Amino acid sequence: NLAPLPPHVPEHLVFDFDMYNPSNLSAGVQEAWAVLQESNVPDLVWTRCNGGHWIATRGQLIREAYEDYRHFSSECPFIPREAGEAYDFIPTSMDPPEQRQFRALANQVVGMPVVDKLENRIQELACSLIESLRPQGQCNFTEDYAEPFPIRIFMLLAGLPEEDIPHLKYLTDQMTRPDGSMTFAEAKEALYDYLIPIIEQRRQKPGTDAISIVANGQVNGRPITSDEAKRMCGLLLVGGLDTVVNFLSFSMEFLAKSPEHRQELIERPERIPAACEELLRRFSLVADGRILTSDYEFHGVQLKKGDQILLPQMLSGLDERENACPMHVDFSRQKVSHTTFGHGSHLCLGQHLARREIIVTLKEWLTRIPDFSIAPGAQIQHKSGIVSGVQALPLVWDPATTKAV
Ligand code: HEM
Ligand SMILES: C1C2CC3CC1CC(C2)C3
C-alpha cells in the first residue's frame, strides 16, 4: 500500500522502506533499519509507504537537517503527516526562537539538578525491584523491571497515581508504536481527557511535582497557558514511559547474550559510563523527522516545500563513516559517535534522567545477578515505530549464583 510517486522524485531515489514494519525485523530492529546504509542505497532516498516521504540515511545529513531549523521545521515531525500535524507537544513541535522559553521550563522539571535530587530514590528502587526478582531465577524483563522501573520514577516526579500507569502507557504506546486500534489524534485526545483535570487542580493549589511547576510556569514575562501546560506535560508523559522503558530491554537482551560483556562491567566498573554510551549508540531507537517549510536543495536533491523527511536518530551511530564496526559493541571505543538524544536546538532534556537510570540498572543488576540468559526456546521480537522496542524478554537464572547485597 504505496502512494504514487510525486512529480519531483527521481524514481532512482526510490527505496520502499516501511518504518512501521521494516523487512528484517526477525533479525532485529536496528539491523532492520541498517539496510538503509547498504552500498546499494542512496544517502537520501524517498519511500512510498506511510504516504511517501524522504528519509535521510547517514550521520552527516541528519546532523545537518537537525541544525538547519529554517527549511527543516518541527511543525510536523511525525510521519505519517496527519499524526505529525495532529501532534502538538511542546517544546517539540516548535522551532526557535519560540522554543527557547518552553524548553527552559521543561528543563526546570527534569534537568540536571532535579536528577541529583532523585538519585537515591532511583537506587533505592533499583535495588528493591532487583532483589525481589532475584530468588525466582526468572523474570519477564519487559513487564518485570523495564515497565516498572522508569515509570514509577516519573509517577514519583509528576506526583500522579500508579493506578494510572496501564492506561497512559497504552496511550503512550499507540502514539509511538501505532497498532491501529487508535489513530494519533484519538490517542492525543484521551491522554488529554486525562491530564486536563489534573492541570486544573495544580493551577489552583500547587505542589512540588513536575506538573505543578508546569501549570504555574513562567513563559516570556506572562503566565503559561492551560493549553501550553496540557501540551508540555503531554510530552513528559510519553518521553517518560516510552524511551527509557524500551531501551532497557535491548540493553538487557544484549547482556543476556554476551557473558564477556557482563564480566567486563563486573570487574572494571570504571567502565559503566563508557559502556553506557556505547550501548546508546548501538541500541538506539528513535525515528521522527521534520518538514520543509519551503523548496530547498539538500545535497543535490530538490526538496519541495511541504514534503516530510524522516531523520532517524537510530542511524547516526550505526553508520560506518562514523563508527567502525557499527553493529559490534565495544566498551573501549575511542569515540562513540551517536545522536540517540537527538541533536540540534531540540536536544533531549531528559538525557540526564535517562542516562542516570541506565547506569543504576547496569551497576545494580550485575551486582546481584552477574549471570543470567535467555529463556531456552524463547524467540525475542522487536517492534519498529517512532520509538522501537521489545515484545517481551523472558530471562532465566540460577538463584544459587546470585548474591543479595
Ligand atoms: C531512553 C532515553 C531517551 C531517548 C533515546 C530519547 C529520545 C529523544 C530524542 C531523539 C529527542 C529529540 C526530539 C527531536 O529532535 O525531534 C528527545 C527529546 C525530548 N525528550 Fe527524550 N528520550 C529519552 C528519554 C527521555 C526522558 C526520560 C524524558 C523526560 C520524561 C524525555 C523527554 C524529552 C523531551 C521533553 C524532549 C524535547 C526537548 C525539546 O523539544 O527541546 N526523554 N528525546
Ligand atoms: C516526542 C519526540 C519524538 C519521539 C516521541 C516523543 C518522545 C521522543 C521525542 C521520541
Image (cartoon, rainbow, N blue to C red):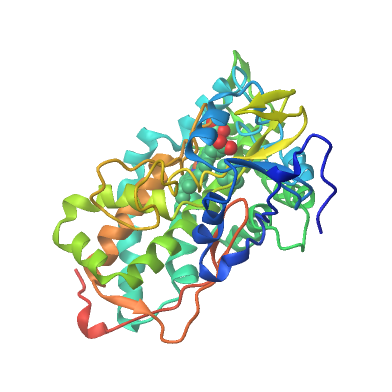
- The N terminus appears in which quarter of the rendering? bottom right
Residue drawn at 50 percent across, 60 percent down? 31
Is residue 236 positioned above or below 265 on the image?
above
Residue drawn at 19 percent across, 68 percent down? 405
Residue drawn at 75 percent across, 39 percent down? 10
Residue drawn at 62 percent across, 19 percent down? 98
Is residue 36 positioned above or below 45 on the image?
below
* Location of residue 212 in the rendering, given as x and y in whole percent from the top left corner: 55, 36
Is residue 180 positioned above or below 216 on the image?
below
Residue 24 appears anywhere in the view: yes
Q: Residue furthest left?
A: 267
Quarter of the image for residue 229 reads top right
Query: How many marks do you count on the picture?
Result: 0
Q: Is residue 114 left or right of residue 91?
A: left
Q: Residue furthest top?
A: 221
Q: Is residue 362 left or right of residue 111?
A: left
* Location of residue 266 in the rendering, given as x and y in whole percent from the top left corner: 18, 63
Is residue 17 positioned above or below 206 on the image?
below
* Location of residue 133 in the rendering, given as x and y in whole percent from the top left corner: 35, 75
Quarter of the render that holds ligand 2? top right
The one nearer the camera, 234 or 226, is 234
Quarter of the image for residue 368 reads bottom left
* Location of residue 80 in the rendering, given as x and y in whole percent from the top left corner: 74, 46
Q: Is residue 175 left or right of residue 159?
A: right
Residue 236 appears anywhere in the view: no
